[PDB]
Image 1 (cartoon, rainbow, N blue to C red):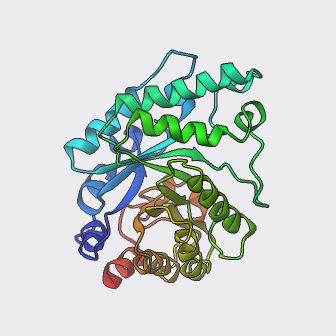
Image 2 (cartoon, rainbow, N blue to C red):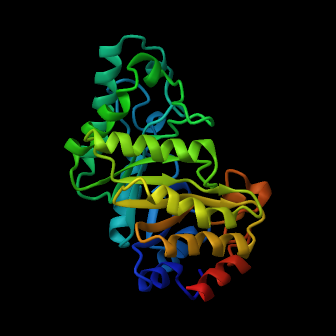
Length: 301
């Protein structure tokens, strides 16, 4: 663990948290738990709350992993972001094979309601719909869009609000890093339209999986996302190829400049455990020591 907590420092600047993705497999190995306890104030389950993990067979739920994380976070005073109710990836075959609208709508609502109810009042925010947009700004043609239609989004949010009215409901996506990107403009436009129609969308999550030198672009992209009018915006799965301090400080600054940005979550603790470990994109190295970017974020805060 680093002696200085990026979480406590960002809290002092008026933000809610600086967190990280994790799960039981990480918390029970290496120095992961000690680092999270000392330096971060929020956790997102990396995989334990996904559909394949929680409902592997229709109606036969599995909460072992998710329960471990929620209990661990509560005991350790860490906020929790529930990660992902409706998504086309890590989706069991039994769901994807359904072609009937009514059958899929009930399956989707039952999945959302069951998971949100089990942890009602303990989860700060949920990524209700994940990666619903194509790169051109059109809606991604997943089983949900194809079978239920465009209304699957409003239905998912309505159901989630009813399940736990205490949770902030987010739509999460990636490649929202440049203000000029077709996807960035589309999600801002669509979220304004959905909110105008009464859809309960509290936040826009920007994954922020960056390439080296891209951090400067989020200084302009984040204010644009905040213009959709949602109560909150957040950097949800930050990592940057090469991990330069310039890119990391720019992302932190973008959040400080935007009042509605409530916090940042980095996607993992140590480099070798990253989904793209080859790029060494995280704040702690393979020996669990803080990298120059960690210290640069501390000094900036």
